[PDB]
Length: 126
Ligand SMILES: [Cu+2]
Ligand SMILES: [Cu+2]
Ligand SMILES: [Cu+2]
Ligand SMILES: [Zn+2]
Ligand SMILES: [Zn+2]
Ligand SMILES: [Zn+2]
Ligand SMILES: [Zn+2]
Ligand SMILES: [Zn+2]
Ligand SMILES: [Zn+2]
Ligand SMILES: [Zn+2]
Image (cartoon, rainbow, N blue to C red; front, side, top):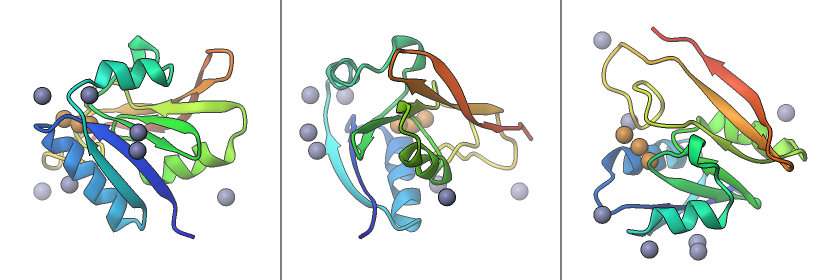
């Protein structure tokens, strides 16, 4: 029973492809949907504009916005109060966005049923 995740992304989003490859390297079964219309996907899942990123995934009913680490997807699965988790933007050093030894600090921000932010994980910058 490997975990399954459905990813929609643009055809020319190479970081997005890198992130999928990090998930498969962690054992996820990934379905890759190339879609030119990510605004439709994010709006369909109620991804708040302020949390947007390069790609939008769905696992077990909850959305996964941006370069969320796999360990944080596992925490997202366990949390009945959260409808999604996001890494907004494209911080360098997040999985699939790695560009050397330096890393932007970033957080994984869960969203609650009623729309509140909730910090799932914090990643210190190097
Ligand atoms: Cu990127
Ligand atoms: Cu990306
Ligand atoms: Cu992406
Ligand atoms: Zn699908
Ligand atoms: Zn679909
Ligand atoms: Zn395009
Ligand atoms: Zn489309
Ligand atoms: Zn556990
Ligand atoms: Zn990589
Ligand atoms: Zn180095």
